[PDB]
Image (cartoon, coloured by chain):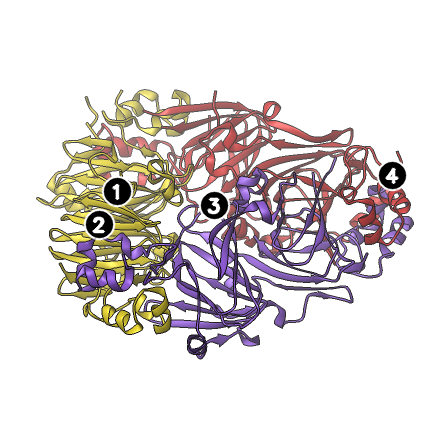
Chain colours: A yellow, B red, C purple
Amino acid sequence: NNPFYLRSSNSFQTLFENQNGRIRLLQRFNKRSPQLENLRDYRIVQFQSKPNTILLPHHADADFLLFVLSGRAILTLVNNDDRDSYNLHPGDAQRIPAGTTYYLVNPHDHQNLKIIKLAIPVNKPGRYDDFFLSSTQAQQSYLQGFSHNILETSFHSEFEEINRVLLGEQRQQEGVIVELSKEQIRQLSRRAKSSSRKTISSEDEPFNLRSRNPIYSNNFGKFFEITPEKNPQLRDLDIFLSSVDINEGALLLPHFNSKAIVILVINEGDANIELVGIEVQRYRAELSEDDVFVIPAAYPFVVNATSNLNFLAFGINAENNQRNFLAGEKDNVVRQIERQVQELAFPGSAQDVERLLKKQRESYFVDA
Amino acid sequence: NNPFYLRSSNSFQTLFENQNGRIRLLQRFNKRSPQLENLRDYRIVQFQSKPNTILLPHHADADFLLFVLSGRAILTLVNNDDRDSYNLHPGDAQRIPAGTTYYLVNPHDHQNLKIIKLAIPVNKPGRYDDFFLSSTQAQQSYLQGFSHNILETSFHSEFEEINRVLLGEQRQQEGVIVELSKEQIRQLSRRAKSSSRKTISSEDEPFNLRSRNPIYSNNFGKFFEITPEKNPQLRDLDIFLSSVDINEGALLLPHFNSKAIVILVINEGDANIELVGIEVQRYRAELSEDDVFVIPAAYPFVVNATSNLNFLAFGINAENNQRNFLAGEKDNVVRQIERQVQELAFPGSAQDVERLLKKQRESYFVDA
Amino acid sequence: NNPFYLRSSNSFQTLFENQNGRIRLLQRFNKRSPQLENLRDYRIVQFQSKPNTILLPHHADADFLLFVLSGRAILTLVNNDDRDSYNLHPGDAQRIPAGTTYYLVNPHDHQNLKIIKLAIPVNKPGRYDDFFLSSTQAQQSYLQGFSHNILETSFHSEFEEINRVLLGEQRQQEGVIVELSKEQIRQLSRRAKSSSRKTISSEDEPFNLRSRNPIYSNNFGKFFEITPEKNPQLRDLDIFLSSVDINEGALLLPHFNSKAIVILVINEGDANIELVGIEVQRYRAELSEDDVFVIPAAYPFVVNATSNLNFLAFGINAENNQRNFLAGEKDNVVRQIERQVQELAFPGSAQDVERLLKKQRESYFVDA
């Protein structure tokens, strides 16, 4: 019973699912246990869709920070007078302001589209609703919420017309993810602007973690990260994003984040995490794809890859976060203690400590 | 019965009242429905007073954003070394910072003074107290909480003297709102600064809503709005103000605010409102003068004026809010949706959708 | 039963205590009484250690605003690639960011080190844990929370040696505050930056409150105060500091803060305090060394020193706070009400109210 571990097979609630894909909402971080209370305004959403599909137009009373784990997506946000459309590849991230109507195409022919969105609801901490403009066997259009008179007046048309064309009270679709012809992807994709090296510090276009060099990278791992200091959209959310690769049989060395609260999601592969909290308490879990683990701020932890692994991290409370390592040569806080203090904090000579800590000649990732 | 509707006769508690005026406090938004949790920091206050009256000096442990619905006022904020007096007219808005001693005159001879303020308590979320300096048959001066010995040392006088002059333990007024002579309004007014075109973006002086052009206006209504982007006091509170007129028998077309939570207050007239939440849920209400209605962020709604109508609205969480209309020609999000997506999202041809969405030819306000 | 008085003897919990000093954590501000709910993210920590001692390296999931009440300290913050020592004197303040490893030396040979820190926990509002790197008879190292296998791989070493050097499962020390030699204090002191007049507005270094002229000073009292206006560290936190000396038999005149919530801490001496809330409510307490008292924003209060007195104040919600006195010549709000409104608000003529407010020729501090 590890409250910071959310196994994908029992921590989600399906919101919409059919033959074309699925939208699952993670359980609230706080309802499991009160140690995660300052995550109460955040939810994780998972979106997955079959090739040649579109998620129909809708908005939500929540900001979404979306990140493409794998596949390809056309994300099109439709404003009251304009339309922004973006071509997303793995590693691409983009903020969707609360209450923006958008739709989401998977234009690939064989690859499934895998998206995670950090949701930030506006009206009530941690709970929001999807408002679907469309009419569909799964859900009613929100335009159906207005009376016959009000609708007739607003559309300057008889109710029969507006019901036949918009609502369908057979003629309507089956779900909120539906299939596309080739011709329509051919037209829906061809206005979509793609992320670039020149977008890493843009205020509107999508940006990509992996388009820049890792902060740490050796023969055993790669750690990509983008922080509020570099991106104004992450600056506004006070969030950082990381995407880290670990070879099978290697680990990310024990470390902790000074002030950021980390939500990590397994994208591919499996891994063993150990987490330390306060006499000390060991928190352990064995993870697989779609699993979620949360590292409270300043709690040390380690990630031991048991297969080839990638995970995404969301860093809440991100501003001026420091990643402090407890082993290895680079970024090792323990080795920065004055020698006389090392002497008194541990049982052992200064030189006996100094020698023990110099042994691991590598940094960040090592072989296991 | 609609948790977002707050009928004026059932939703206000009277804080003070007598023959000269009255002050009432709206109920906590998050008590009425735990659906309005992110409004818990805010309260609505309604102030009304007769001609040639004054609300005596006091302060509160809340920020106020006050707005003059109708009538005329002199607002005087007293500082520890200074004093600022303002000449206020219908549409005039001003922030009173938390803990600022002030008093408030109705200088008019025949017109009642009607004011609404948005309260933002400091010590407890959504709860604050008024601290009256005056000693009055309806509340004790907060000077009276100090003991006799501390009073005498503080003021360097016998308690008899300070009691006689400050407290009167008859010689004191009957309530906190009391009548004024003509001579005194004469004296109290001749240093009051008035709002003006150049005050539209001050941090000091009152700014008037309806002194710029309306952002939408046609033959059926007018929509005045000032946002954080134009006025620095509104930027600090992160609030927008609107004032909107609607001719009897017209309506504000269905629309939603992308991210702003709106508290609206009926200033004059009668209206029916329809609000759509989530299968859809219809929330409907018939409103009149002094009633309040709350629209959560990204919930669509309509407002149908059954008599000539003016309402005031406060937008919580206002920065970069977008107003998205669902019908009419201008700022219509539905009509920004790509055509092939309209075909897949509604049960009807692409031309069938385009043809209906053009039928309504007006924007914003239409005749019912 | 004053819900704003936090008597030392029954409002603290001992976190650590041994022969060389002790750390204590004040009870939650809100668990006391629902009146202080907007202080639920804050906690007070009292620190005290004997001469020639050191607090062993640790970090916490909280920001600390620490303040030296009396004595001398070397504060060393160790970063992942750097180290920063500071030489602290009474009045010195420094923010220790969350998750910053640090150790705290008392280099004095006779005087104790009295420190208070304002904690702002990161993961759960108002609740944090200390993460000691050291393996001591009083607490396990958090490195012990990782498994045998993991620790071997990370430190490239057999578990016997890791255990034999860092953990020691007799060789280790008794508590988290331990004694120091004179060789060691020599060495830990010779790079220790010391606050001065060019750090008053640093974003990094200690700044001394008492190195500037006080804001109020006369023959009875001294009132030093530094605010977020002039120091970026306090600006990020939205906190002011004050330290005020009052001679025995003198008193701080009745006053309120407009918008700041004040946590005061008796450093040295005894005082009677009258607090006034809302008919009016009298709140009284006899304070002495280490007591804590909260003054909600906009509540008038008075400090009557019954022995030579110094206290420290944290002003939460500090930006643009105004201090309004209610007696004396300078910064007296009551003396700024127009004559005619003084005529209406008190049962005494304007001439009688004029004479009585003028009678206290002194300001801020006066003699009892």
- Chain letter of the residue carrying label 3: B
Locate residue B66: give its quadrant. Answer: top right
* Residues at marks 1 and 2, CA–CA distance in whole angstroms: 9 Å
- Lateral position of residue B40 relative to residue A151, left or right: right
- Under mark 4, the amino acid is Gly
Which disc is residue A273 wearing?
Answer: 2
Confirm whether circles 1 and 2 share one chain: yes
- Residue under label 4, please give it: B168
- Under mark 1, the amino acid is Tyr
Tell me where residue C301 appears, x and y as whole percent. 71, 49
Looking at the rendered image, the disc whose residue lies closer to the viewer, 4 or 3, is 4
Position of B57 relative to A155 (above/below): below
- Chain letter of the residue carrying label 1: A
- Residue under label 3, please give it: B318
Give A251 or A146, whichever is nearer the viewer: A251
Confirm whether circles 4 and 3 share one chain: yes
Tell me where residue A195 appears, x and y as whole percent. 23, 57
User: Does the image show residue B305?
Assistant: yes
Look at the numbered disc 2 and give the secondary structure of its residue.
strand
Locate residue B129: give its quadrant. Answer: top right
Q: Residues within 10 Å of mark 2 (few under 14, many from 20)?
A: some
* Label 4 or label 3, whichever comes before in sequence order: 4
Confirm whether circles 2 and 4 share one chain: no
- Residue under label 1, please give it: A5
Residues at discs 1 and 2 in contact (Cβ within 8 Å): yes
* Residues at marks 4 and 3, CA–CA distance in whole angstroms: 47 Å
Confirm whether circles 1 and 4 share one chain: no
Q: Residues within 10 Å of mark 3 (few under 14, many from 20)?
A: many
